[PDB]
Image: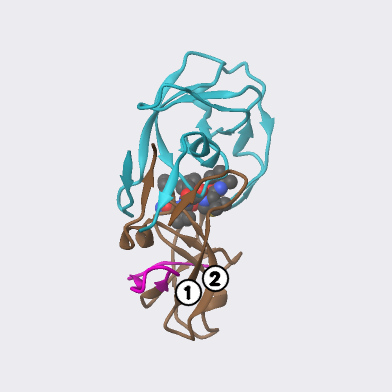
Chain colours: A brown, B cyan
Amino acid sequence: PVIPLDPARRPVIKAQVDTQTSHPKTIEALLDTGADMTVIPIALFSSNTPLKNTSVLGAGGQTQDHFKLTSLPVLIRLPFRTTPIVLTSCLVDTKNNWAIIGRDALQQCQGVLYLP
Amino acid sequence: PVIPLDPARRPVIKAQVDTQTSHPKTIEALLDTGADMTVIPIALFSSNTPLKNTSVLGAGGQTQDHFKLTSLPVLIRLPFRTTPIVLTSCLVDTKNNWAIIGRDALQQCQGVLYLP
Ligand SMILES: C[C@@H](NC(=O)[C@H]1N(C(=O)[C@@H](O)[C@H](Cc2ccccc2)NC(=O)[C@@H](NC(=O)[C@@H](N)c2ccccc2)C(C)(C)C)CSC1(C)C)C(C)(C)C
């Protein structure tokens, strides 16, 4: 669909995420064209699960430990397209539990920004 | 225009930003559906001008001192549309120079995300 843009209202989507380490789960994710890589909560993963360390730059400054990287690809299912996004690797937010669809995912479902 | 989304190419636009505190300047800015509010680098303001302290939460955590809020509206002209975006207030990057066009601005362009 066409998603209008409003400063008062985060553009969100219901995404079903399969981390491949426990059953798939629905999350509300922020559609974010300024994110290089998708971010998913640690709450999706299991207490076991190897995850790599990774340095991440945001508006809040630089961080060594808030975000980790996935060991295995993450499958994402959007409500419309029957065919999953498969991200080879993506970020895992261990501090807050943010959910951010980034351009890695948006490219794979051929998302565009349209400015009239 | 139609701006494709690709994790290796940040989506940018040349924007002419009038702080109303010195000569307008054209800068390169990121198009960012994840940003509530536009960010303009402090370099586009006079050393004289009053700015308001603000706290900002972003991927890197919380920051009291890195961003300031403007005192005068900011006028932004995009290369295609003749009428300026007018933002009552927007964020100022007091450090590392970020130029981020957020949903405040994108709403005024009739900006949208399309996902087929
Ligand atoms: C209140 C701020 N809001 C936000 O920052 C919102 N976000 C956004 O607006 C995002 O599009 C953010 C834009 C950004 C990138 C680099 C420095 C500064 C800002 N992108 C990132 O933080 C992403 N970081 C990156 O993509 C990183 N590789 C990068 C380094 C240098 C220049 C561009 C990108 C990611 C950690 C989410 C993957 C993600 S978190 C958020 C609260 C939803 C503000 C200051 C941008 C309005």
Q: Is residue B32 magenta?
A: no
Q: Tell me whether circle 2 and circle 1 mark residues in contact (CB < 8 Å).
A: yes
Q: Is mark 2 within 8 Å of ligand 1?
A: no
Q: Which residues are magenta?
A: A76-93
Residue in front for this viewpoint, B79 or A102: B79
Quadrant including the C terminus of chain A: top left
Whether residue B104 is situated above or below residue A78 in the rendered picture: above
Secondary element under disc 1, as helix, strand or loop, is strand
Give coordinates of residue A15: x percent, y percent. Answer: 48, 69
Determine which residue is flagged by label 2: A27
**Occupied quadrant, residue B70:** top right
Q: Chain of mark 1?
A: A
Where in the figure is residue A52, as x and y percent of width and height?
43, 72
Give the vertical position of A12 relative to A14 (above or below).
above
Q: How many marks?
A: 2
Q: Identify residue type, mark 1.
A: Gln
Label annotation for residue A16? 1
Quadrant of res B82:
top left
Are labels 2 and 1 on one chain? yes
In-image side of B104 versus B81 (left or right): right
